[PDB]
Image (spheres, rainbow, N blue to C red):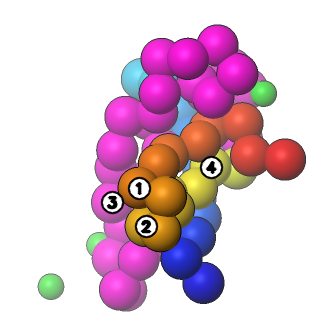
């Protein structure tokens, strides 16, 4: 896919996702409906849209 999944940190508002055999930590958005609101929630980096979302559906 273009989507690379991981889990978010509520304290840090980060997403740690897996891509190319490595883990990568990116800030989540600060937007209300994309930030990490629930610790360890699934999150995704989408390298098609060039976006992060820490409230994936
Ligand atoms: Cl790694
Ligand atoms: Cl390496
Ligand atoms: Cl949430």
Residue beneath disc 2: 47
Q: Is mark 3 within 8 Å of ligand 1?
A: yes
Segment tinted magenta in the rendering: 14-41
Image spot of residue 42 (x, y percent): 70, 50
Residue beneath disc 3: 24
Tell me how far mark 4 sits from mark 1, CA to CA.
14 Å
Q: Are marks 3 and 4 in contact (CB under 8 Å)?
A: no
Closer to the N terminus: mark 3 or mark 4? 3
Residue beneath disc 1: 50
Q: Secondary structure at mark 3?
A: strand
The residue that appears at 47% across and 68% down in the rendered structure is 48
Q: Which mark is residue 43?
A: 4
Q: Secondary structure at mark 4?
A: strand
Q: Mark 3 or mark 1, which is nearer to you?
A: 1
Lateral position of residue 5 relative to residue 23, left or right: right
Tell me how far mark 3 sits from mark 2, CA to CA.
13 Å
Image spot of residue 49 (x, y percent): 49, 58
Closer to the N terminus: mark 3 or mark 1? 3
Q: Mark 4 or mark 2, which is nearer to you?
A: 2
């Amino acid at each position: 896919l273009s989507k690379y999944g991981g889990e978010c940190s509520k304290k840090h508002n980060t997403c740690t996702y897996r891509k190319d055999g490595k883990d990568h930590i990116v800030k989540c958005p600060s937007a209300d409906n994309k930030k990490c609101k629930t610790d360890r929630h699934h999150c995704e980096y989408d390298d098609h849209h060039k976006t992060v979302d820490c409230q994936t559906p």
